[PDB]
Image (tube, rainbow over the protein chains, first blue to last red):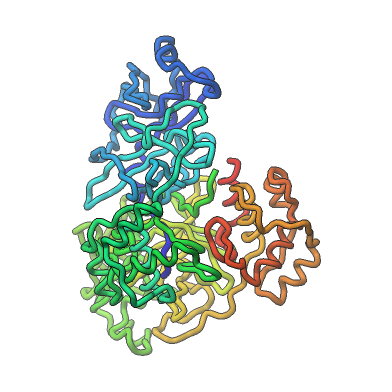
Length: 300
Length: 299
């Protein structure tokens, strides 16, 4: 069973998705307790040109918001910005609010996206946060407000809320404190993403998955120390490898030390030639050590 | 923008998942009404040797089954085989049984898998049915009994239950009528998969997505008519293309009419020459035209 991207189940999250419209703008929000959070650009008069958010808020009329789960309509009793998110106090507590926390995702970490269309959950898939604070997902007009979440040992953390797409196609969102990942502005502007730095952690994990799957052609039987690799990485847009401790059970299971995979990376970064790994034509950094271990052995 | 294999939400299915054990075997079952369905091989006293299902059925002792949700067990009142599925009547109705239907998936069609580990929902991902009736999923020991479903216009359909993995890594399961997709036997035998036939309409969809996503290297100053492509298709493990009717909007926004993409397929089959398309080193037939259209400019 090769390496494919998965999402954790979505059932705890689905009951919290609501439809939010204001003016001609429609998107999704997240309903926990007596509050609904959604991108603040929903109250903007024209999201196509620069927005003066202070003015849009001063002119705001609460009864112009339409917030709904299905046939359930939520009166908005107040609205305030919390960074790039709008927080709407509403007249009903969501009876299906799951127990949860909030946290921010770091470069190289994976999480789940529940893509929603006008208030209706549509799909779910796994993503991985890139160094510049963007993700390579799949969002179309109307998916703003979609929610990113991760479950860790029974704890549900909400971690992302979708805002916009960069000119280069990458996707940008915020955490629930309202800080935009990557620092990008919620405006129609020419901001650039910048150069992305590959996660060595995840690429080493990708190669272990390939070994476990029966592909070993990139195996060198020559090992590169963690220090030599790290100096090489600072100069080739890859992150410094923490320690080799995260791969202990993977190295034991395949018989390949991390240092041999490090040597494989330096060589494979030159180019796969006419060969592939897990059907990819180049190194993949989308899978974390923990994703691979669960997917390959399932002990989580 | 962007193309990813996605799955439809699992909230309706998760409450139906249960742990079913018997002997040294532990796998998953689907709990609907007062019945639990699971792969009948959970009854095998020895899974390393050919299984005689009549004998395992004759000597069954209902008390040896253990069926539970969370740490809560259910009583097994009876057990019968329905094709390769084991059906167990239990002493209790699932109060969370969603409204549902059952249907069979055809070659080239996509559906969702809710991968489960010994009674517990662990992950959700989309798959697509191969010509020989198998899927390329990610199932590891303990995920047998995982469930395949599809949502269409608000109607939930259960379509697959996972049984086993063939020597070549391909995955085999049955429908809810108890028929194994592809007619494979539910035995620990070394049966082969058979020649895999690539779905053409899905490959064109994929190439269209690559165009929309910005890759053009594979597009050339050429066109291969519907009729001639369908001819090459027949002797090169590829299906026939009914019409170009499905691609109107894709062909319209990319500016590449279908017959040009058909030409690309014929020429990529021999290798990408080291290049990639949406990151893959070979052609992908895992996405249907509808799946791609909905993700490209939105429905």
